[PDB]
Image (cartoon, rainbow, N blue to C red; front, side):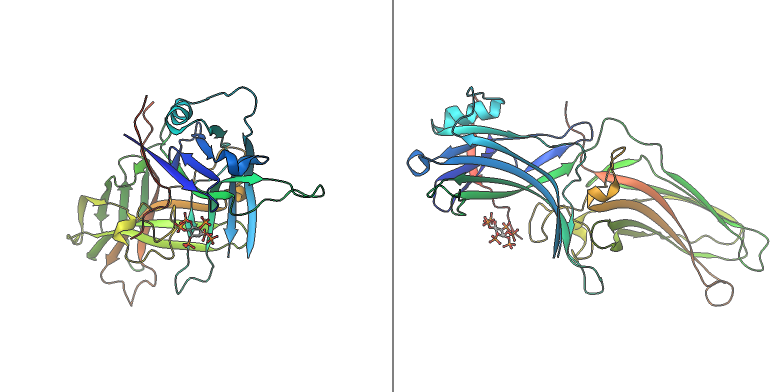
Length: 359
Ligand SMILES: O=P(O)(O)O[C@H]1[C@H](OP(=O)(O)O)[C@@H](OP(=O)(O)O)[C@H](OP(=O)(O)O)[C@@H](OP(=O)(O)O)[C@H]1OP(=O)(O)O
């Protein structure tokens, strides 16, 4: 079956039906919002129902619109053109007072990303919202048109980032250190399997420690760090751990060790959901970590609202240094991108409420 999502206006005059809650962005193109509006003909006689798509960034206090489009759904515009199969089947299944609408995304918009601060975080809440709003318009006096709220339905859809057709090079990084009073160096080489991983896919961090010093590498710790840059209004910055694995081995003096740890960055593994960039509201079940921001060529990054990136951090705890030979500890970073899997190149309908489930 195909679950159709609906939402009824307060006066029950305009009901909206979408085929999805989350619409797919896979770099090359963005999935369009096709849907239908069921109109109570007696409550709308003399009115005009439109449907609009608005993407906007919010901080707080401050707001900046990023994209706006609007389409007339009633009265029917031109030829009754059922553009998509979903629209035609929803009209055949749903009645005669059903009229279709199509709203298309551009390529210069971000994906659904929003964050609510933590106790120690200085910044305020912010996010990027995509709102599908259907509404009716009538005219009592000849001097103005009015838009009542009760004749409107408001939906908050997602623009979800899915993997593109191609992928980047293999992520690698090398680092070296010669501590004070030591002629022999400590070397660290980190490699990932691929450049793009999916939400829930295991990330195998391959660590190669070549220790030529007199000192023992007490600990090897691998982290998945999320870097979040707010690029509108205030230049807030967050760097938080979303996955951690501590290696069981030590590296004795004048020896090498190559081990592959496995980390899985998931929002489900963070009891604290504040201070990190998410793709939805915190209280919602289907909320995940924000996917890696993909800035397209030529588009100024400020329009993206919130920039989200991911990196592996390998931290080495070395003996004989803490407190007498160094004041900073050794680590290195390996960037990668995180997003959702790649898209795959007379229907039966069951209708549910649009409201996302809680937890
Ligand atoms: O302030 P309102 O006009 O009453 O809007 C609310 C509010 O949405 P916003 O805060 O984004 O404006 C709810 O969110 P909460 O503040 O309660 O967390 C939301 O409920 P959801 O959390 O499920 O989004 C609800 O929408 P809905 O009725 O679908 O649950 C929506 O009400 P409206 O339908 O009037 O927009």
